[PDB]
Image: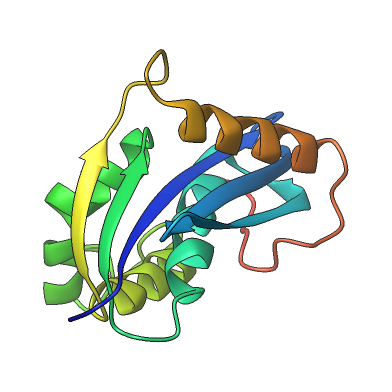
Length: 155
């Protein structure tokens, strides 16, 4: 049987754009691995994506994953947009690349390596680990050490 891993993820940003960061927790057989990093200039949406990307890429073997996050952006992409973008070559009708294509492509790639059960949560009570991810993400945004290379300035 495959390992069944619990993943909790969250991202945040102080502005649009501004410093931002992510936080993710992987739970397996009582063991826990935490991941967090901050970027000098990015956006909330890119951080929401990165959290999920870093968590999934951290798994070195095919797994059963229970991914819990309150990322609306990730949810919409996963249950709505992802399919179409794969059917249009990751480009808008006007041939212009889809926003954050660099990160969406990395996520999609990570997604196809595991059986994922998504648990869309609502930032409140009953989600201790998610709240923990928020704290990690907020502490990383306040002490950024990385450059979000894939970030392209609006217009």
